[PDB]
Length: 69
Length: 57
Ligand SMILES: CCCCCCCCCCCCCCCCC[C@@H](O)O[C@H](CO[C@H](O)CCCCCCCCCCCCCCC)COP(=O)(O)OCC[N+](C)(C)C
Image 1 (cartoon, each protein chain N blue to C red):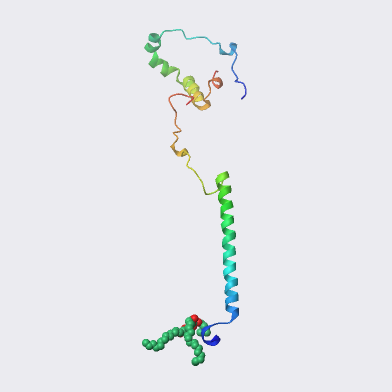
Image 2: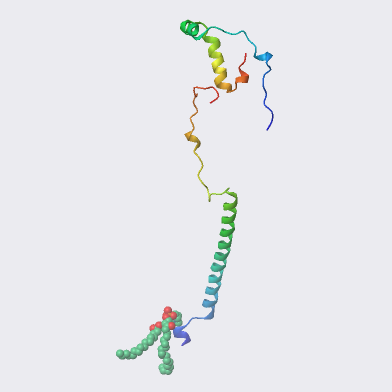
C-alpha cells in the first residue's frame, strides 16, 4: 500500500516548508504595504495619493497693459 | 510682516507739466517723436522692475 499509493515523509515535510515560507513572506508584505500606505497618505511625498494641482503651463508671462501685472 | 518702504515727500518733487489734455493731444505726435528715448527708458524700467519706487529718476 505504501509503495503503490503514497510517498515518503520527506516530500510532505519539504512541501510544508515551502508553503510556510511563502505564507510568512506574504504576511510580512501585507503588513509592510499597510504601513507604507499609512505613511504615504499622511505625508503625500510618495507616488501614491497625489492629488492634482494647477498646471503652471497655463500662466501667461506677457506684459499686461500695466507694469505691475 | 515687515514695514513698507516709501520715498520721502521731498524725493517726490519735480517740475510739473501743467498743460491741459487738449494741449497735450495737439502736440502728442511730435512729443512722441522727439522725447522717445527717455519715455522708452522709463517704460522699460516700469515694466521690468514692477515697482513704482524704483523708477523715480
Ligand atoms: C490483494 C488482497 C489483499 C489486500 C487488499 C487491499 C485492498 C485495497 C484495494 C481497495 C482500493 C483502496 C482505495 C483507493 C484510494 C487510492 C487513491 C489515490 O490516492 O491513489 C492514487 C493511485 O491511483 C490508483 O489508480 C487508484 C485506483 C483505485 C480506484 C478503485 C476503483 C475500484 C472500482 C471497482 C470496479 C470492479 C468492476 C466493476 C464492474 C462494473 C495516487 O495517485 P499518484 O499520483 O500516482 O500518487 C503518487 C504515489 N506513488 C508515487 C506511490 C505512485
